[PDB]
Image 1 (cartoon, rainbow, N blue to C red):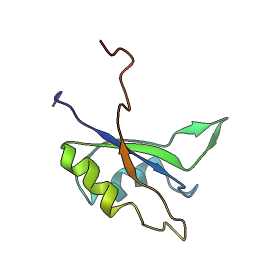
Image 2: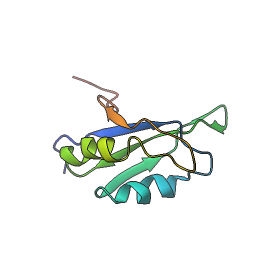
Image 3: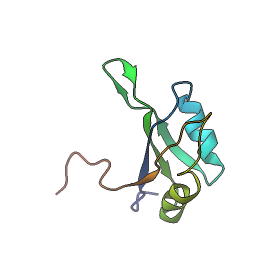
Image 4: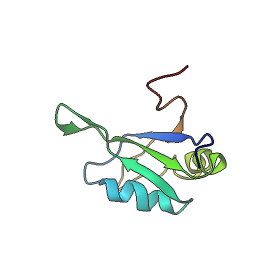
Length: 89
């Protein structure tokens, strides 16, 4: 670890969708390291991120996941560059 992992991003997620799901659900593609549901004004906005062990798996999930209707709700899973990093040189 500590090489250059990459985290993706998702939008249009169903309320029910709990952090646990984001991880497990994605666990199918590969090993999920991080999984949280970004909240706004105290209310969720069907949005979150997911990190993997390898870079290929990160973008891979964006191809498999992206396009999956969760209970009749389509989501857009894409690669999220420069996701973290408060101090960039």
